[PDB]
Image: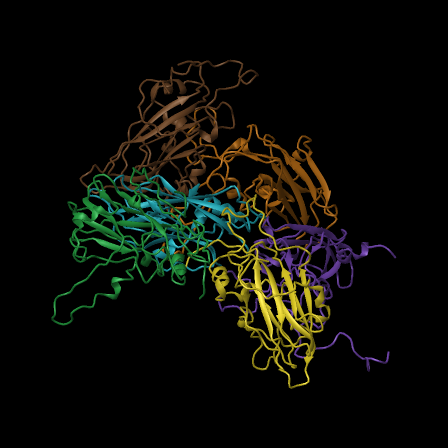
Chain colours: A cyan, B green, C brown, D yellow, E purple, F orange
Amino acid sequence: ETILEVNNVPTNATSLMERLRFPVSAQAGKGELCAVFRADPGRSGPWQSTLLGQLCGYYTQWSGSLEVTFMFTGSFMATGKMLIAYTPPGGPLPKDRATAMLGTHVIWDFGLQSSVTLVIPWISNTHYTTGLVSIWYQTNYVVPIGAPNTAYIIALAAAQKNFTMQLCKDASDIL
Amino acid sequence: LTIGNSTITTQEAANIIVGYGEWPSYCSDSDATAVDKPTRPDVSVNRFYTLDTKLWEKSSKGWYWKFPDVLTETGVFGQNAQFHYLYRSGFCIHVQCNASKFHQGALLVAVLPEYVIGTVAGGTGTEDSHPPYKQTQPGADGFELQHPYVLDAGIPISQLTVCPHQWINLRTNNCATIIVPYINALPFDSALNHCNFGLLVVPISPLDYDQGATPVIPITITLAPMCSEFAGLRQ
Amino acid sequence: LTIGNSTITTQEAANIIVGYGEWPSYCSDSDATAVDKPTRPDVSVNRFYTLDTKLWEKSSKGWYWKFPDVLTETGVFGQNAQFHYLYRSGFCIHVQCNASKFHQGALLVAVLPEYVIGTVAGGTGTEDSHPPYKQTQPGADGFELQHPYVLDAGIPISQLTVCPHQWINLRTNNCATIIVPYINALPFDSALNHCNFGLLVVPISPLDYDQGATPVIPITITLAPMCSEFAGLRQ
Amino acid sequence: LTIGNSTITTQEAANIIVGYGEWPSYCSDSDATAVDKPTRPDVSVNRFYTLDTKLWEKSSKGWYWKFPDVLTETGVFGQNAQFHYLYRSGFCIHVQCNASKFHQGALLVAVLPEYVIGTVAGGTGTEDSHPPYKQTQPGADGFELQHPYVLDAGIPISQLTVCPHQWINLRTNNCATIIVPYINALPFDSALNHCNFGLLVVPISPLDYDQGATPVIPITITLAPMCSEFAGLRQ
Amino acid sequence: SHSTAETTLDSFFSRAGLVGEIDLPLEGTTNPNGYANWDIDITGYAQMRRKVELFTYMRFDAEFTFVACTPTGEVVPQLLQYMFVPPGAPKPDSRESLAWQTATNPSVFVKLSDPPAQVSVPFMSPASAYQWFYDGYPTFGEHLQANDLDYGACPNNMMGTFSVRTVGTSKSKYPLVVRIYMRMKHVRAWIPRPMRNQNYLFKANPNYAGNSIKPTGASRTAITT
Amino acid sequence: SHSTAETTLDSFFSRAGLVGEIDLPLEGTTNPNGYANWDIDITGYAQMRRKVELFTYMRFDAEFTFVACTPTGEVVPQLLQYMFVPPGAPKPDSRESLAWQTATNPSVFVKLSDPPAQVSVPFMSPASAYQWFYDGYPTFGEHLQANDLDYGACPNNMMGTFSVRTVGTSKSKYPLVVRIYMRMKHVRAWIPRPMRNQNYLFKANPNYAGNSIKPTGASRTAITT
């Protein structure tokens, strides 16, 4: 299990650390928070942060299943609900929250504080469109007085026993 | 209950409570009640249909739902109940509100069979009647009551507890779960035309915070329909 | 673990985690690896050396330690490791932070064998190199990182978890404990000249309070070195 | 066959002939092909889908279909493969034509796996390409051939019988039945993007009547998909 | 004549065939670069395409041999480089490219004095079998109207591509000609198809002319032999 | 694709890689002597450094190959000498030095006419395993303050160096280019590390820039794909 930089947005070294992290706040309610983007490691993107995503760059095409656990960093007294929904390849991004409920999806409550594991069944490279995981405000981030009205989540991922890789492939960074 | 997609794990105190004392059953059909025999497994369409989560303010006056209705463009159930000739099903619904140990209020999740909710307007000034079309077909989002003391129905909540009910006191329980069987004169009725059933969420202690805390409290509704009745038709 | 002076009692969830899956062992010496045989009991010098407790602010960017180093004028271990010819030992370290159920943040206590931490300056304006002397011999107090994303080492924390690690989420655990065995090419090396080992404390969620609460959060470090290797020398 | 709705009565002559000698099978899953485990009854989706019946004149030159496509907004089968990411199924198709005992002609119902049908136009006077988009996703209605001798593929019917075939000679049979299994390099592909499979209805003896008898000949097509593969998704 | 060995797919395919003739002039208008990439198509050997379009799906390894000479045929003391790059790997762009040192791009160094090099490329596809034409759009998902001729074409049907160089920082001394030969080995095929009868237009679709010819004529009438 | 074989350390490393490019022109300004020592860096193959700093400790034999040619690519009837000298042994200083005759410095004599030489260098380290970086001063005993930048480099990790000559009492006649390729054999690795993300400055310390780049960007916002 290694960190997935879903918030692959800022390029400032002081805010370069904000990449691992992605926010939730008491502001927006039941609307839309974040799709963790593609469920594809080797495609240029957020997965390049993972150890998995990098070694996939050292090969060509793979087949397997992944598990992506999310971790909540908010206060103890903080509470709320989130539904995480995977959208398989081909299908466009779900129109709304309720649309995500009609498929494979998991409502995450902060009662089961520790974490919540999302297992994506199958992804493959046949070199586009891949699976999508979207995280929705089932409800807003409610907090009592004394709790920060905004909180942060870390997403870290890895591969299961069915993960296999292809032929060696080289493409680096250095000169 | 491991029937459906994703649940929510709880330390679940005995918040379990069955409608009138009998569990949801199927249909007894070894006579001539229907010569065609509808066949349906338990986890095909018993997905956890969770409506959109609603807010609970201090000036809130309670909300209601109808169950044969609530599924329209809602779920593969609605893609099934709208085209189907006749309908029947039981339900397992779990009302959960997420709040702080600093917020206080009092909820009554209650279940009411035949819910004819009124209604009235002013007087004889412009029109004499016309209760709303949207009284029926209330969406998942809707709807607010108008006079909670009478449920807009000329009947006091003071005695609603005679119906299968369950309390949500933010002092103690954040979760309440109530299971309802089927309840009708005919063993098989039609769906969208008659809302066989009504769900109520009425506040008694209208919630109170001390500011600096989110004034909005989430009431996430989660539904699980048991003992449905279908087969298939046209389109 | 009742080996040393004073411990700290916890309801200790399974925060126990061993380096790479094998417990700290001793030295296998029935050949000719050393003709002199060092002898050492387990509780003489395995005192709980707790460094000074450090603060955790919002603008904190993580801290690191080196273990053969950390003992210099530190403990009877340093009075032992500095005069001794060669060194070897395992460790049991317990990182504990004391915070409120109102403070939130995210820590990654992680362990890294060979820690060569850089470093770089500006460019070719005044001098071209000179990484610091105090890079080595970091005192108990020190030291802050410079670029946590690269650990000042050109290597992303994003994948540090491949090393024996443990999370401290102030939502759940206030304590994390990680045990490390010895890890080196030679079964016996020298001490203060080579820091065999590095300890990391990196924040991911940079802590947040809502004011009126102590903006400083204590990370008390407690160390317990197992399977040392000594005998005695001169002065 | 007690799987489906309504049949067409036969004395059940042996016009049955299977693709390559093996029945359509299911999936072998005691390995790691899918962490999701498919669940499926024998009579759920196997309704007898009969497409529109098309006419057959003297100047007829044959028609063709593609199968993974033909059900898209067609029947509850297409509403399922369109919503599902991936697909697999076998088919049992019964091509039946209604004619007089005074009519004469010869049809060859044949089945061809990968049917990439061309094609060419006038030339390069105004445009160099334009293959039709509507070539694929052929509705029940389509399609007419263009050059039956080469199947618009530069490939002779002269050897078409090398593929799964069945004859319709009005001397004997007005009915023909052919069964096809799943056939692909990958065990699971998508539907509407790739037509894995093609059906041909080509005349050799181009029909002849002596007029005063209905000159239009009905070829009613009836399909029955076996060993499908789905589960359910979103909407 | 009871013997079925010459009717095996293997015997039907096991033969080193010329599929590549690579030109490196001293200078000219072919490639002033001194460098050439050869996408590894079997259709280069003309008759082979009809010979294999007998089937839908098939599978094979490939034995490659590289005989190189001058256009005269003079064997010449030049040391050259054959480079095979996998489907994933990028193809080299320049003579001075970075791709030549890329390890996952296997390279072969021989002299012309040394007998022709010989290597074997196995079955590369991510599918269970190769496919000569895919009755669908090779794009996954909903269609984009950027491309519409990639029809029938299977992209993972590509088994890589070959690159050739005269080794060295400086230009070659001699005009050389490399010829590329393909041998097919462990073959398994599947769904049988009727064999081609019309002439080909392209090498990506069974396109044909707007006027059909007939595989045999000149018969006068059916009664007279 | 059920095989973990290409995820084996051997397969991850099993490929002869170019690590050295030594030029001996007839005369110029590079090295006019006809003599060259090549300190044996593995980092010569560019990408290899990040690829091995995946681990802390590892261990392996090394198979070296020597393909030599002219810049022309002309194979030339020249007899040359490859000499491997151990870490302890001194390196030759002049073309007419004695070190060329030091027997315990193994030598290889081949012609360019002779196909590329192939030798194998075993695990040389005095440690139980190789080591990529030493978090200490490489001096035994307390350090002398001559050093200010000598940090991290492991001296007993040095596996020797290769030296090349144009054999003969007199200077070479032909312009030559020797190329060195490395393949790693019986590989065993140990402690896993996160992989490099920034560019390297030196090959004696994992130093980084005073301005960090990002291993993946151009993402606009977390909501937009």
| Residue D62 in picture, x, y percent from top left | 64, 75
Query: Can the viewer see residue E4 in this picture?
Result: yes
Q: Is residue F72 left or right of residue C132?
A: right
Rendered view: D172 above or below D77:
below
| Residue A118 in picture, x, y percent from top left | 42, 46
Q: Residue furthest bottom?
A: D212
Rendered view: C235 above or below A50:
above
| Residue A167 in picture, x, y percent from top left | 59, 48
Q: Nearer the viewer, residue D150 or C8?
A: D150
Rendered view: C58 above or below E172:
above
Residue at image coords 38%, 33%: C133
Q: Nearer the viewer, residue B208 or C170?
A: B208
| Residue A120 in picture, x, y percent from top left | 46, 48
Q: Nearer the viewer, residue E24 or A70?
A: A70
Q: Quadrant of the C terminus of chain D?
A: bottom left
Q: Nearer the viewer, residue E188 or D196?
A: D196
Q: Is residue F46 left or right of residue A116?
A: right
Query: Can the viewer see residue F225 in this picture?
Result: no
Q: Is residue D71 left or right of residue F210?
A: right
